[PDB]
Amino acid sequence: EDESLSTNIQKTTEYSTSEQLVQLRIACIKLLAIALKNEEFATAQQGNIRIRILAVFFKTMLKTSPEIINTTYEALKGSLAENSKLPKELLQNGLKPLLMNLSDHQKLTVPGLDALSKLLELLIAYFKVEIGRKLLDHLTAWCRVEVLDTLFGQDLAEQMPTKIIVSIINIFHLLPPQADMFLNDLLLKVMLLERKLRLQLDSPFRTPLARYLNRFHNPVTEYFKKNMTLRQLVLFMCNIVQRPEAKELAEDFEKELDNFYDFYISNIPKNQVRVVS
């Protein structure tokens, strides 16, 4: 009910003006991106006028509509080719409400984490990899027992904690490539969450974990070779590799079958009680 209109108010009309408003917002975003792609037309005019619309581009990554999010992500990835150091103040104001939403609030949203991923496809302002610790803290606080007791009795694809956990696992894919000490914790937590929901087939959060695993995919082969006595890890990895979102983890396994052969052949006579496994 503010200055977007002249005579067509929005407190008595729904879906007749909201779609037109969304199309108007994405059209203005496309026009600003096309104008910003032109040199000396919006770049060197008035000094900081591209900063004034990059603040708009960071302010529009909090709308709940995914279409506006995808459009402004296309605008950012088309407009940040002409990057500069001079943006240093709006980064402490653009991605700041989302990172403050990420804190000890315990009520995260799905398009908020979607916009967090779309902003997380950059490499600046989160050089400290401590976002993963808060993400695992929120993941452990979303896979509790009391919230999973609300999951009892219904399905597992229309529930809000399932979508939140899927988004949390999904934004582990775009983390900075440091020494991922959150590999073992994340893998054990997803396997314990699958065992606690007692599902032994395809699960909702195996596709974001496959997108996490095929990205690094060098230490996960050694983590797999260090744990082959676990039946559930073998079933989990054999279901992950067949997914089309793990096209490079598949060829990482095809050149290591003989190591698996020598492992199982040399480890049969040590036990001789779990040979069928």
Image (cartoon, grey):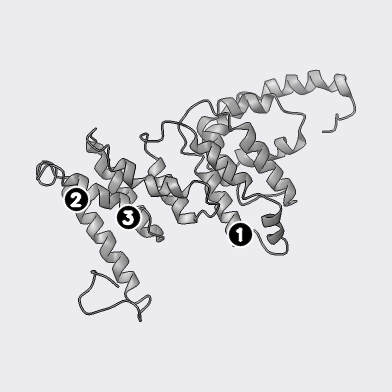
- The circle on residue 45 is none
Does 81 sit left or right of 154 as displayed? left
Q: Residue at x 21, y 45 (%)?
A: 51
Q: Amino acid at mark 1?
A: Ala
Question: Which of the two labelled residues, at mark 2 and mark 3, occupies the earlier sequence position?
Answer: 2
Q: Amino acid at mark 3?
A: Thr
Does 96 sit left or right of 102 as displayed? left
Question: Which of the two labelled residues, at mark 1 and mark 2, occupies the earlier sequence position?
Answer: 2
Q: Secondary structure at mark 2?
A: helix
Q: Amino acid at mark 2?
A: Ile
Q: In terms of image quadrants, where is residue 69?
A: bottom left
Question: Which of the two labelled residues, at mark 1 and mark 3, occupies the earlier sequence position?
Answer: 3
Rate crowding at label 1 as few (under 14), some (14 to 19) or many (20 or more) other CA atoms within 10 Å.
few
Label 1 – label 2 distance at C-alpha? 39 Å
Q: Secondary structure at mark 3?
A: loop
Give the foreground label among 2 and 3.
3
Rate crowding at label 2 as few (under 14), some (14 to 19) or many (20 or more) other CA atoms within 10 Å.
some
Q: Is residue 246 visible?
A: no
Label 1 – label 3 distance at C-alpha? 28 Å
Q: Which residue is mark 3?
A: 60
Q: Which residue is mark 2?
A: 34
Q: Position of residue 214 (x, y in %)?
A: 54, 35
Q: Residue at x 25, y 47 (%)?
A: 54
Between residue 41 and residue 206, name the one nearer to us. Answer: 41
